[PDB]
Amino acid sequence: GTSLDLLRSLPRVSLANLKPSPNSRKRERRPRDRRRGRKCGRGHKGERQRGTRPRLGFEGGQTPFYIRIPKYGFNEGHSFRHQYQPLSLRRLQYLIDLGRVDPTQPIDLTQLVNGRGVTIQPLKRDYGVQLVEEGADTFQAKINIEVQLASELAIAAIEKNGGVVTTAFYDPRSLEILCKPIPFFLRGQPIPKRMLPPESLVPYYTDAKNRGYLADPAKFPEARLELAMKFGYVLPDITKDELFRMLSARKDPRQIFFGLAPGWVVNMADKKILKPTDENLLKYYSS
Amino acid sequence: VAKQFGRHGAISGVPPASLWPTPEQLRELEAEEQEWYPSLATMQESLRLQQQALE
Amino acid sequence: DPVLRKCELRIPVHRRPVQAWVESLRGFEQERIGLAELHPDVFATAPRLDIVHQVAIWQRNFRRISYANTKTRAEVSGGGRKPWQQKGSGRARHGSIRSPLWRGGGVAHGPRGPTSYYYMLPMKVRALGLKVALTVKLMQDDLHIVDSLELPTADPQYLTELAQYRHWGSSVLLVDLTHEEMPKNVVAATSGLNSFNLIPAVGLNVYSMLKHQTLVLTLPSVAFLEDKLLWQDSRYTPLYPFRLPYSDFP
Amino acid sequence: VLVCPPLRSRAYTPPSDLQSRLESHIKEVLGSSLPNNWQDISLDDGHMKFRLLAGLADGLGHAVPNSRLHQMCRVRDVLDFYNVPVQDKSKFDELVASNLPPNLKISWSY
Amino acid sequence: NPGFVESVDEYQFVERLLPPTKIPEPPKHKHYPTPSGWQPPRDPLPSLPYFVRRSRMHNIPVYKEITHGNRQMTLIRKVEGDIWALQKDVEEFLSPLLGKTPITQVNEVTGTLRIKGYFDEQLKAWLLEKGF
Amino acid sequence: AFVRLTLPPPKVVDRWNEKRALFGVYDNIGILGNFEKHPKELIKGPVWLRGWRGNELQRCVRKKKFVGNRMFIEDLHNLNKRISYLYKHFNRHGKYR
Ligand SMILES: [Mg+2]
Ligand SMILES: [Mg+2]
Ligand SMILES: [Mg+2]
Ligand SMILES: [Mg+2]
Ligand SMILES: [Mg+2]
Ligand SMILES: [Mg+2]
């Protein structure tokens, strides 16, 4: 460019020629000159001038504002409430379009996080992803996806195209392994089991209408049909579809990863998977 | 010591069988599991009783 | 047999490549032995001298630990007792012989212990400063691409004379791919020279490219540098530190 | 027994006839006896660019700087570049030999 | 007898989990625009004096920005070539909508053009037609 | 005031000693070395402030954490008193609330 041609003429760049970007630094003012010296910006003698004014929120001796308001449980149990990151079909379509979420294979929270499509924070009480209806009208992809929460309209968009959506619960410990699997294989521990939902969440994940992972499989076809009629689309028979096996693939309710059983150890250095043989240890994991 | 096996695999020298719980360790895990994590059948049964009382 | 080199990674379609003369140090007159192509986004980025200033500051300030210290009025020997009574003396009121006003007293606002100036610039910013610095040397005719650092003799006189014959600067910075394989002839000659410094390709930085007038890069180091710096431009944010296993990262 | 040759001057003045000297090199390198429209021949080919530029530097003595190689897209650019003279005289050096007025005296203390 | 058993037949699923560090190049689509709305830069390249590059996520680098909580601006980044030529085109393009010449700042060092007000949507469609 | 009556001895700085010549090398050990080492690992200094920065109150507490139990009786007494001085200033005294 023309800028580089200017460098050719100009003298060498060196440590003696450096300069910061203009206005990059403000100048700090010492209390030395008459303008900023003398009383030094503090005012005439007094409590605020000696530096001993009362604490923040003190109002000179009347009951402060933040003390005379009734105490109310807006934030009770905030640290215990569950948080589900929202994923919109617009974001899902956009990720697929640019190749960042491969639709050929099943989509699980690992793949979504692995494609920088969602950011999961188990420390801040993230327990998964909830599918968001936004973008349903323009959603034209056939995919198999597992999400901890889903909405009635969000499910309809996935299924109408012939995809599969199932809702699966991951416990706080399992989610952290799911989100960052490799920073776990490096520890050297065996893969833990996946714990069942708490009593409060059991109804949601055992219900077909929500596509629960613990729900009765025989009851799905009725649920799929009713949703199709309500939203005015024809339910597509996915058994005929060539990639039916991939669409129907589902991990065991006590399994975190698709091809890895609980209890195995992943020797990444040697590209091996140590597996136990003991009976009590195999009964513990297979339970 | 485990951390050495996961990073470096076999060359660490950790005896593989030492990566899994020991007999006494296994008993602690199961006993703790029963106390704090009920089975699916019990959870559904407990839920049903609450609904009947509510009804 | 001209030594012709091409960028391994794909150059943007809209930008044409930049080139430099490949050189040899085997003889005084072997100035042009090949023609080389350099990725425009490494050696032809926009000239940003504010960023070069930023990186040069960081390299000089995050290492700084100041060991200056002073004693406060509490840490000076003695001083517990009241010198005289407050009243009935005609003297100025005092509470200690070690206050800041007194000779031998504590320092009111002095340096306090060892202090660190540590901070980290964004990794992309520091990588950019290596790209900007490389453009500056090329566009200002101070960068000399060489095929290898092999030298006919180990006498330091040869290296200095070669620099004068070719109109190099008083100070030359030489880069080789890896420390282990650097030729013995080059080590012997440069070891005794203050102005000619030899570093491995992993030691290249903005501060040393501004202290040394002319930069000498072997062809393998050019490919080494282009790969690392370009990788920064089409990368995700780190899920976890880049020393942990990744799908495609060494 | 490596002995440095004398240091060369950095001054270059266009030769008598660049076209004659340049075209001769082009004919040797290209070998087609100066096809018409020679000036617009592209130098994108690496081997052609090296042979043409490398030969010119040896003959005339003036070499294309690393900064300007990418600009030599076509033969016209190479011909234009060699048309600019290069002088090693400093701006001070020019003043000394500039027929200064008799009341101006300059002395070199370096 | 060790209480374990080594296998090398299931390390395909572990490889599936490893994450990438390079943003993948978008896959070729049969029909453009893509259902999201994304469309790649046109080829052959535009012949304008200036070139606007795509971000690492392969989008047009137009960003809505706000300062002071009320000063609305739109920013065009990654502009190569004659940055001043791009301003002239933007002023002509946006003047009919506003009815007056738009206020702009050209930062030649960074290579970005800054416009007062929100015009990202109109300025993204505009660039798409030019093929940037 | 009073001034020197003779010039002080000339000060000579050799700019191409090994420390000055090779200053700044291996500062991109991370980006140019596959991130095996962070540059902050190359800092040499007190144990409690390598790759770290803080205000005086923060520096006092961190020194106590790292070497507090290996400190001399007189020093630990002074360090502890400095913490309490700085705690009361930064949390009770100043212009801004
Ligand atoms: Mg101040
Ligand atoms: Mg978050
Ligand atoms: Mg005392
Ligand atoms: Mg007392
Ligand atoms: Mg007192
Ligand atoms: Mg003293």
Image (tube, grey):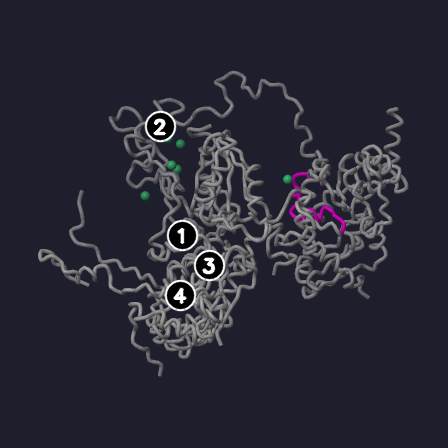
Residue F80 in the magenta stretch? The answer is no
C-alpha span from label 3 to label 4: 22 Å
**Camera-side residue of C235 and A282:** C235
Q: Which mark is residue C160?
A: none
**Camera-side residue of B15 and A176:** A176
Label 1 vs label 3, nearer the camera: 1
The three-letter code of the residue at mark 2 reads Gly
Chain letter of disc 4? D
Are labels 2 and 4 assigned to the same chain?
no
C-alpha span from label 2 to label 3: 52 Å
- Label 3: few (<14), some (14–19) or many (≥20) C-alpha neighbours in 10 Å: many
Name the spot of residue D100 as percent of width and height, x first: 13, 58
Name the spot of residue C58 as percent of width and height, x first: 44, 51
The residue located at (75%, 42%) in the rendering is A147
Q: Is residue B54 above or below residue F49?
A: above
Q: Which mark is residue D78?
A: 4
Q: Which mark is residue A3?
A: 1
- Position of A113 with respect to C41 (left or right) is right
The region drawn magenta spans A105-128
Check the picture and name the quadrant holding the N terminus of chain A: bottom left
Helix, strand or loop under label 3: helix
User: Quadrant location of residue E3?
Assistant: bottom right
Q: Is residue C237 visible?
A: no
Q: Is residue A8 above or below residue A72?
A: below
Q: Is residue D46 visible?
A: yes
Helix, strand or loop under label 2: loop
Report the residue marked by disc 2: A41
The three-letter code of the residue at mark 3 reads Phe
Are labels 4 and 1 assigned to the same chain?
no
